[PDB]
Length: 60
Image (cartoon, rainbow, N blue to C red; front, side, top):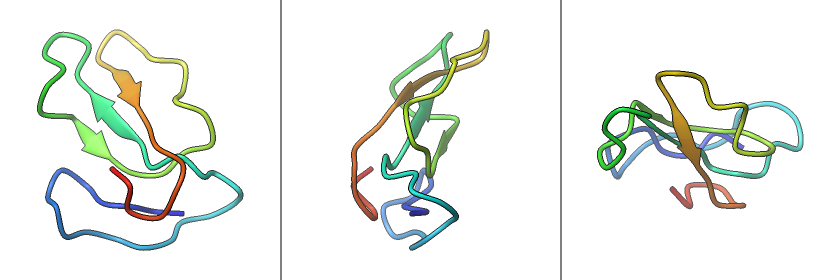
């Protein structure tokens, strides 16, 4: 599972059973994300992130 980055037309498949197409939003300004990629569960969000996510190839 890889999915799309900030742009609508992006990538296809990255490692393991990480189903969620992440939407890595900035903790300080959410709306337009930092990155858009691949993950199992929306991760442990640090001072610079608040991750959004959806279960299949290119769903973000």
